[PDB]
Length: 541
Image (cartoon, rainbow, N blue to C red; front, top):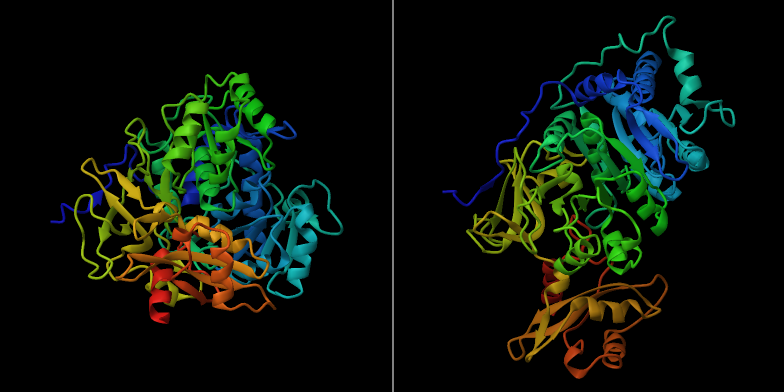
């Protein structure tokens, strides 16, 4: 008891049998048979593509890859900005159990190399604007046998398109509607290899088995935790396909037969006009697009009467920004949640209606969550703050070729340890403790760490900084920082302290001093890791 474990309710829609490829194949085939059902719409070029087109090409890419030689022992990379084509090789691979590692058109060569060094792909699908970078990475990773151009019909600079590639390898009388996807073990066959960003150091490869997608397809249909399947539902999605939010909303939308309208370059008017003209029900935004829309004054120009929901997925939002965005859009609130790459998608989610101010949401079906004491690891009770831990069928199988990082994160009982601080209240709402609102407190007077961090990031020789409060006794807290120097530059602690003092009131002085590090510790979300910053400076002095 262990009435202190917060458990998700029963799913509205049971977990269905099959691989992710099989459930996607089955749903999309039914939508393919209704002419004119729109799967994806490109807001920039205004072209629609139907489920019939989308199913037939994905089916053909699956068989073409199968005949080329790929099976559950291979991985592909899809390297492209959001596009009408992005999900064709993705769906094709899932149909035959080939693992997919997404990457973006505009990631630098260094980022692509490390990502694809982890995923080690036999075949790369790339858009025209990513070709040169994939070529340059290929000469450094010779497991890359074949490059296929996504946004072309003819061959392109000697390389095959998806359309000519399919034609080289399909059997003579191939029938898209007789194809059957590979059956295989959903628990161990890897569906996605997602990149991590995440904590400190190099991005890791998060391996996600087909099961996580299949569980997510239950969430997508849920009237409480996902989207109610009404006909002519359209989503305006402005989030990258190659992070969890965009990858797994989209796969779920395809299961549901929805129209997915895409924007890959954000523009204010195009966004608002697309909400209006496409009669969008739900919009997906990256967190800093929420702050953008808190400032927009054009929203009242548009007829947004069909708009029911703006969502941020796994990213928590401050109460201030969310309320402001809800108010600008005349919504009762916004849909928030908390998830990690390592959880596939959001595992805490705002329940429909059941929103509470400042809450991030509630535990999703199939999941349980707890908070634990940061010293004993013992499960805490109501309204007590500890580390958030979660357990469920959407947790990754692990990091690709790094069981050390895996076992350090997931315990012997399957609890993932988030590194983030949370509590739950009496109604089972969760709250994520935001580092930015934890004020440092010096003889009465409080300072936001991000204020000082901003002062420090201003200096030409300071590359990165993390500010937290050093416990003192005399004092309460002394503001103190870990500082990452810019390559080449030399600074002393007294130099940095003198610089801050010359920019802040005397209460906000950096009396705790400075500890030079190589990197500011970050959590799995990418936000600064205050607890570890504090540890570093305690150990130092």
